[PDB]
Image (cartoon, rainbow over all chains, first blue to last red):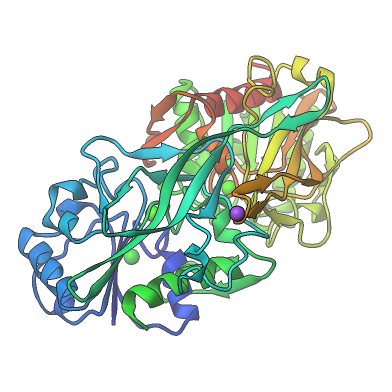
Length: 252
Length: 252
Ligand SMILES: [Ca+2]
Ligand SMILES: [Ca+2]
Ligand SMILES: [Cl-]
Ligand code: NA
């Protein structure tokens, strides 16, 4: 019982996670970014709610209060970054009561960071890799790249699992050599609890343009097509990482 | 006088280049990826044709002949990489007489390379940066990242201006340290002539998911919205690079 809201439409960006969930044989309801969500039965019957490029204004205030209560009673909640997540440009989730249950502080000014140079997903601490979301993935052998994120900060009682390290390489024409220098870092995946529900904030996107190299993570390809969506072909480690994220939040 | 074919639709990926061209005050015609192109007035009146995720099967054999003759008579042609460019998966341009005028050899089997780790665009030689396309861009100080490319090879009489250098960083949780090792390199931008026309083969995409960090290249932002397309917000250097590429090919 999963509700996925946003990423424009199935025929566009939502096709990625909808396709992943179809390949996992999960059942889900889907709401596109231009359709609203009100209090009631559709919201009531979920065990996992995923908000990704779904603007705050799409939810009525009473829908938000229902969701908040449901998460405290055990429902999983995950937010995935994008231009209409967190604060973004039209996300505005900092202005909602849902901010109280998310494990990150959200800015009240534009929080979008777009990377024109290489940025790697890296575990936050040496034992972050023991977390079920991070297990059995090649963080050391093959750190994946991301394209951007919303700038968010872990709350005091939250656990940061992944960072994003920004690199600013330079190239010498004369010597034919690239110099790697590191420049900034940002929280990338933060998890926590609200009552008996689990919550996760992923700062980057599951779909373009911010998902970046992560969408192709691995040496193999996973192909799928959610009903109503375009066919996808994506990395095996991409599928595995998002599956482990959503399974943990859902307490699968 | 510009004809731009492919990248699905204006409301989706074609909005990027359409938005750039609108921001440059250029006029253009546009054909979506599902719409065929036959011999006609629409093709005849052009000075620049851009093919980008436009499958070979959409162009009639007579249209291909018209386009080849026009290019040899002075019309510029640019192919931009993607899954339905070059050979790709459904591109199949190697099968066409258009292959004759392009400045690269196109494979007869899947040529798609997707980068899950950092890949940098780099000038191919010391004097490449003197080429009009590459002038006044910070190739040394800020080499941009791309997400993938079609594997293509420069024809003998053509000039390779940019390479893509594949990096395979590894991360040590113990040392808190990233080690940067490079691997392969691929042609990224190859230019030539066919009769009196100029031709260009860019191996990566102008739009997601392969354009990667290049779409955000620069410290500043360009905003635009082509008629019928979505609003875009992209890098200043991204705009400048694609403008210079297309102006060179068009002899603008
Ligand atoms: Ca998104
Ligand atoms: Ca494309
Ligand atoms: Cl939809
Ligand atoms: Na250590």
